[PDB]
Image: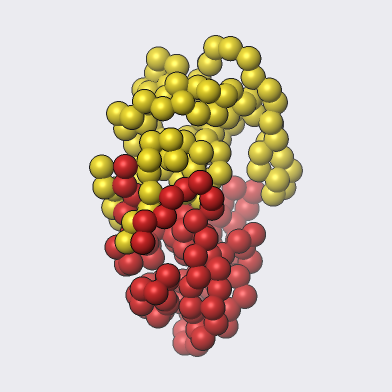
Chain colours: A red, B yellow
């Protein structure tokens, strides 16, 4: 689709058998999601950095549907003020900025 | 242009007679810029909210060129880890998300 930016660009994602809402956030490098139990191995990753770091679990090559596009990408899982789709997954769905 | 998201979408902005770099950030409601002295009246605004708020100066109807597009928009001025173009200015330049 083409998403105008008058409102927050919140979209439905399907991940690990759950549907969720997440923000399409081009100011985020990585994708961070709140409350999802994903199968397979993870490694700990530090994110944030302002005030301290936040530790999260990094699962790679994760199947995720963003707005009806089935893609594969690193998802970071742990505490977040909001679910965020970062650039890493926006590239996989072919999402560009246009004007 | 069409901006792919493999790298951070950093663009040149011209504001109050200076050229600057800022991030096109669709996860930011407002536009926040570091070190710029803008003429005219402002009001104090609280932004952030996690850990505390950050006080900044809000100047409205500010002339700004983003990537060669001359637009008018509210700019918030004060301390920021990076210069951020928020949705408020992305709408003015006609910037959408596309996939």
Note whether A69 is above or below A1 in the view shown.
Answer: below
Note whether A98 is above or below A30 in the view shown.
Answer: above
Residue B34, x across and y down, in percent:
52, 28
Of residue A50 and residue A81, the one placed in the foreground of this image is A81
Residue B18, x across and y down, in percent:
39, 18
Residue B97, x across and y down, in percent:
38, 53
Q: How many marks?
A: 0
Residue A15, x across and y down, in percent:
49, 79
Query: Where the N terminus of chain A falls, by quadrant?
Result: bottom left
What is the quadrant of residue B54 in the picture? top right
Q: Residue furthest top?
A: B39
Please state if B78 lies on the left or on the right of A40 as rendered.
right
Residue in the picture at 54% in, 34% down:
B32
Of residue A63 and residue B95, the one placed in the foreground of this image is B95
What is the quadrant of residue A94 in the picture? bottom left
Q: Residue furthest right?
A: B52
Residue in the picture at 53% in, 16% down:
B38
Of residue A28 and residue A14, the one placed in the foreground of this image is A14
């Amino acid at each position: 689709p083409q998403i105008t930016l008058w409102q927050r660009p919140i979209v439905t994602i399907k991940i690990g058998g759950q549907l969720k809402e997440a923000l399409l956030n081009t100011g985020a490098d990585d994708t961070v999601l709140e409350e999802v139990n994903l199968p397979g191995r993870w490694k700990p990753k530090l994110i944030g950095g302002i005030g301290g770091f936040v530790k999260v679990r990094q699962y790679d090559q994760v199947p995720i549907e963003i707005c009806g596009h089935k893609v594969i990408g690193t998802v970071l899982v742990g505490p977040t003020p909001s679910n965020v789709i970062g650039r890493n997954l926006m590239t996989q769905i072919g999402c560009t900025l246009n004007f």
